[PDB]
């Protein structure tokens, strides 16, 4: 959700969008 370094969730696509924090 935030703009951190580790993803919050994963989609059935390629890469995730938002990050922790």
Image: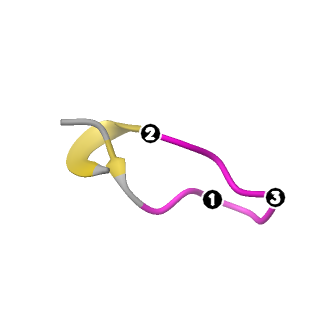
Marks 1 and 2: in contact by CB < 8 Å? no
Secondary structure beneath label 3? loop
Secondary structure of residue under mark 1: loop
Q: In the visual, does 12 lie left or right of 9?
A: right
Mark 2, Cα crowd under 10 Å, few <14 / some 14-19 / many 20+, is: some
Question: How busy is the neighbourhood of tag 3: few (under 14 within 10 Å), some, or many (20 plus)?
Answer: few
Q: Residue at x 22, y 49 (%)?
A: 2
Name the residue located 55 percent from the left edge and 43 percent from the top edge.
Answer: 9
- Residue 8 got which mark? 2
Tell me if 6 is positioned left or right of 3 in this view: right
Give the secondary structure at mark 2: loop
CB under 8 Å between callouts 3 and 2? Answer: no
Q: Are marks 3 and 1 in contact (CB under 8 Å)?
A: no
Q: Which mark is residue 2?
A: none
Whole-angstrom CA distance, mark 2 to mark 1, is 12 Å
Disc number placed over residue 15 in the picture, else none: 1
Q: Which residues are magenta?
A: 8-17
Please give left or right for residue 10 compared with residue 1 in the image.
right
Q: CA distance from mark 3 to mark 2?
A: 14 Å
Task: Name the residue carrying label 3.
Answer: 12
Q: Describe residue 6's horizontal placement relative to residue 15 as left or right.
A: left
Badge 1: few (under 14), some or many (20 or more) residues near its Cα, within 10 Å? Answer: few
Q: Which of the two discs, 2 and 1, sits closer to the camera?
A: 2
Residue occupying the point 32% across, 50% down: 1
Which image quadrant: the C terminus? top left
């Amino acid at each position: 959700g935030g703009a951190g370094h580790v993803p919050e969730y994963f989609v059935r696509g390629d890469f995730p969008i938002s990050f922790y924090g």
